[PDB]
Image (cartoon, coloured by chain):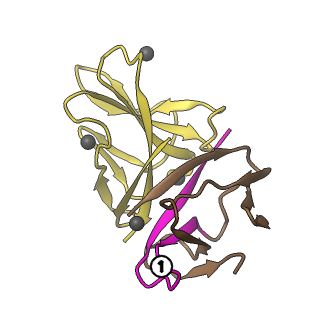
Chain colours: A yellow, B brown
């Protein structure tokens, strides 16, 4: 279980520091209620060869961009922010990192 | 800046894993709010037991569990670790 502690100014945009190896793959999620037996919601979806923030689940004014992943600095009300890291597009083997924010 | 991710069943007792290096002293706090500079309320001096430190598995409503780690007993040179809970 790994944990990335980052700092930003609450309610201003923040480009999240990618805790995954940068030349490989990552996918950003919210884990509902930070409960591992609850759903894992992808924050970004592919539309036209590009990633854009999900629109079919309402998580408010949280995700600003998916290129690169940028949030409005806040803890998401819905749950925890989790990134899944993988060397491979198939994502069959991976590890997760939870990202937590101190407000500056 | 460091956080420790741990897992427990929400609202049931959890013996917290030491987030400090072996041999280091540890003191436990609830942080008042969400800023790094915020004052801390020391525990033991939500809490199920103080030996070993055992909590009711939950995020405190005031703020995060923080552990202060210090090699020397005088706690002059220290580092704090925020404990973050995933719920099972
Ligand atoms: Na990285
Ligand atoms: Na969180
Ligand atoms: Na997969
Ligand atoms: Na630290």
Point 55% across, 68% down: residue: B67
x and y percentages locating residue A83 in the rendered image: 40, 37
Q: Nearer the viewer, residue A35 or A95?
A: A95
> What residue does disc 1 label?
B72
x and y percentages locating residue B71 in the rendered image: 46, 73
Point 72% across, 76% down: residue: B44
- Image quarter where the C terminus of chain B lies is top right
Judge left or right: residue A5 versus residue A46: right
Point 19% across, 30% down: residue: A23
Q: Nearer the viewer, residue B73 or B18?
A: B73
Q: Quadrant of ligand 3?
A: top left
- Image quarter where the N terminus of chain B lies is bottom left
Is residue B68 on the magenta stretch? yes
| Label 1 crowd bin: few (<14), some (14–19), many (20+), radius 10 Å | few
Residue found at the very far front of the displayed protein: B23
Does the rendering let one see residue A2? yes
B22 over B24 or under it: above or below: above
x and y percentages locating residue B22 in the rendered image: 51, 59
Q: Nearer the viewer, residue B57 or A55?
A: B57
Where disc 1 sits, the SS reads loop
Residue range (magenta): B63-88
A66 over B57 or under it: above or below: above
A12 over B39 or under it: above or below: above
Point 24% across, 20% down: residue: A48
Does the rendering let one see residue A74? no
């Amino acid at each position: 279980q790994e944990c990335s502690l980052q700092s930003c100014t609450q309610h201003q945009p923040y480009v999240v520091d990618d805790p995954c190896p940068i030349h490989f793959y990552s996918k950003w999620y919210i884990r509902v209620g930070a409960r591992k037996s609850a759903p894992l919601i992808e924050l970004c979806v592919d539309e036209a060869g590009s990633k854009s923030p999900i629109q079919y689940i309402d998580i408010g004014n949280y995700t600003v961009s998916c290129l690169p992943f940028t949030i409005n600095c806040q803890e998401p009300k819905l749950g925890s922010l989790v990134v899944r890291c993988s060397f491979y597009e198939d994502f069959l083997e991976y590890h997760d990192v939870r990202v937590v924010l101190d407000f500056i």
